[PDB]
Image (spheres, coloured by chain):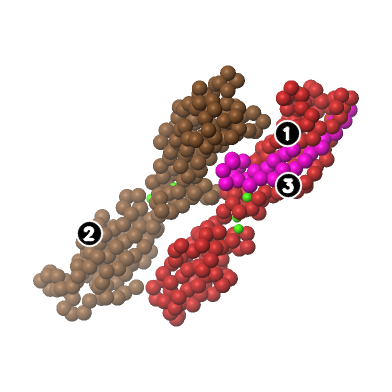
Chain colours: A brown, B red
């Protein structure tokens, strides 16, 4: 938990209240005191003894990296050593629900449209880290109304939110029989893979032409 | 003490983690997980959730550990759902209440049932005989509970036709086409008198 002044990177989970110092910098005479600059945000502090710490739980969605610099000073306040870059990587936790860009979508599809060919897109946004499951979204049709004998007329690309006819929907959609369908779409984060995830829903009304 | 979540059925394309200190790895390594002498931790071929879903590893410094390193093996759809029977023999009373089950068909899926990979969707593929394209039978697409329709309750008549065959399908990925496996099974149903 101590060592020379040099470029270093520390990884700290957002939402963790501090319990111990991050690091102690040691610098031989003529290193008197230490100075901390950069994206301190009144969170990151260095003491005279070279003790580096953070004073409150971070939030990746306020700042996802804190670019700091540490320098060793002498008696006259004059830089002796560094300034060196000290990087804080604020590790993501799943603390944001995914939200649909619309609570209601209005679409239309032609009667004999190709199966798999998109005619509408639903999208959601998640403020968590997209390089992690926390920010990786999975789209599902949860309801089709009306639905005949459990045959799905519509399918959604689970990654992209692209809504297209199924094989059966291509074959069966007939505006005279039924001019419109309502889909309820879910989105989950954690890539749709957990129970331990957040979810949103939207409604899509679709006219058959 | 760290957790890493690695999909099964992927050839390693990245290291798991570089520890900064000599390191020893112990625990459920299964000659797949390796740590270099200087703490580069990595896996040397594709995991299989259905062989081992968590790998409980320990990393020690040589003094500092051992620490539990947990590998959560994330599921992919690599198992077809299967019915518990290839043939079911059912019986339903004439005028039985619509929607009241009289038979269950079941499937199991070796993939994770907390994911779409293990999430099954039951359908009636075909009712024989069928009159005028009217379904006498319905199935609960979550449970595989088979019951009469309103039409079936009103029409089934063992004097006119005492037996029907259903072909039932089960799909995983919650029954959507793309990336899903499927099984089918036969149900013979006798209609008894009221
Ligand atoms: Ca946050
Ligand atoms: Ca999220
Ligand atoms: Ca977050
Ligand atoms: Ca497997
Ligand atoms: Ca499966
Ligand atoms: Ca699997």
Local SS, label 1: strand
Give the residue pinned by disc 1: B126
The residue mark sitting in front, 2 or 3, is 3
State yes or no: residue B27 in magenta.
Answer: no
Decide if residue B181 is on the left or right side of residue B44. right
Sequence-wise first label, 3 or 1? 3
Q: Chain of mark 3?
A: B
Asked if residue A163 is positioned above or below residue B79 in the image, the reply reads: above
Q: Which residues are magenta?
A: B167-194
Disc number for residue A7 = none
- Asked whether residue A78 is in view, the answer is yes
In the image, residue A38 lies at what x, y percent?
Answer: 22, 59
Assess disc 3: are there few (<14), some (14-19) or many (≥20) residues with their C-alpha within 10 Å of its C-alpha.
some
Quadrant of residue B168 within the rendered picture = top right
Disc number for residue B83 = 3
Asked if residue B133 is positioned above or below residue B12 in the image, the reply reads: above
- Cα distance in 3D space between marks 2 and 1: 69 Å
The residue that appears at 36% across and 66% down in the rendered structure is A20
Assess disc 2: are there few (<14), some (14-19) or many (≥20) residues with their C-alpha within 10 Å of its C-alpha.
some
Are callouts 2 and 3 both on one chain? no
Assess disc 1: are there few (<14), some (14-19) or many (≥20) residues with their C-alpha within 10 Å of its C-alpha.
some
């Amino acid at each position: 938990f101590s060592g020379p002044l040099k470029p270093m990177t520390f990884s700290i989970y957002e939402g963790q209240e501090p319990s111990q110092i991050i690091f102690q910098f040691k610098a031989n005479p003529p290193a008197v005191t230490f100075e901390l600059t950069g994206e301190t945000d009144n969170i990151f502090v260095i003491e005279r003894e070279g003790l580096l710490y953070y004073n409150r739980a971070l939030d990746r969605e306020t700042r996802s990296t804190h670019n700091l610099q540490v320098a060793a000073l002498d008696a006259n306040g004059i830089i002796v050593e560094g300034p060196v870059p000290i990087t804080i990587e604020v590790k993501d936790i799943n603390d944001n629900r995914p939200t649909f860009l619309q609570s209601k979508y209005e679409g239309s599809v032609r009667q004999n449209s190709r199966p798999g060919k998109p005619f509408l897109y639903v999208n959601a946004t998640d403020l968590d880290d997209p390089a992690t499951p926390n920010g990786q979204l999975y789209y599902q049709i949860v309801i089709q109304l009306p639905m005949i004998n459990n045959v799905m007329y519509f399918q959604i690309n689970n990654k992209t939110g692209a809504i297209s006819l199924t094989r059966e929907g291509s074959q069966e959609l007939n505006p005279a029989k039924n001019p419109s369908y309502n889909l309820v779409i879910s989105v989950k984060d954690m890539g749709g893979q957990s129970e331990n995830s957040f979810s949103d829903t939207t409604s899509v009304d679709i006219i058959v032409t």
